[PDB]
Length: 212
Ligand SMILES: CNCCCC[C@H](N)C(=O)O
Image 1 (cartoon, rainbow, N blue to C red):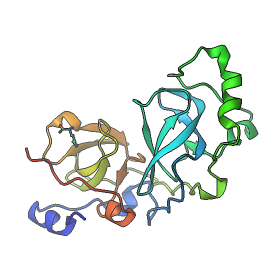
Image 2: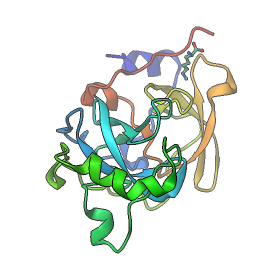
Image 3: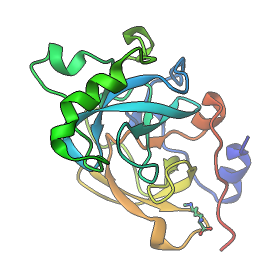
Image 4: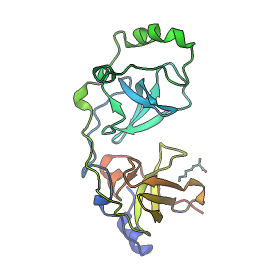
């Protein structure tokens, strides 16, 4: 557990208030189990809804892998992400499940492939998907404020970070102790940012500043 209180004191800094974030007041419970299948937007084509399997759990997050793809493009979603749903959600809504972009077979093998993987599959029930947190009505972040941020280059990691700059609805996230190489701009609505103390509360590891 990272001592934010001591760190905000020695850096003469403020943590961005919780109201800045599209996150729940309390970290949502994670009742997902490794092996459970669900529906997710393919990060490599966000128009596609694909079958994903939980290959890891960490705090309120799921590590996901798309069935029929590869093990090199896993992605992390919170249990209250709007980009994940129970199987059957896509169809109920007038849509069709797609092969992942990294699909290991030819496309005409898809319809039969879907049947094989869904056959007696462990599926996440709809009741363990958590509700979408309320969003801020505007960008309430201020320059200099600290937070917890997913390192998008190593998304398993949530790290000590600072708001460097603000342009309208975008905030510039910088990683304390790391070269500007891990910096990024994101929307203030980003699911990848959390108030200080959130990880400790969700049992997710929290990276201290880098040694640079
Ligand atoms: C913002 N977090 C940075 C983590 C980067 C870790 C990387 N493997 C390295 O050691 O460079």
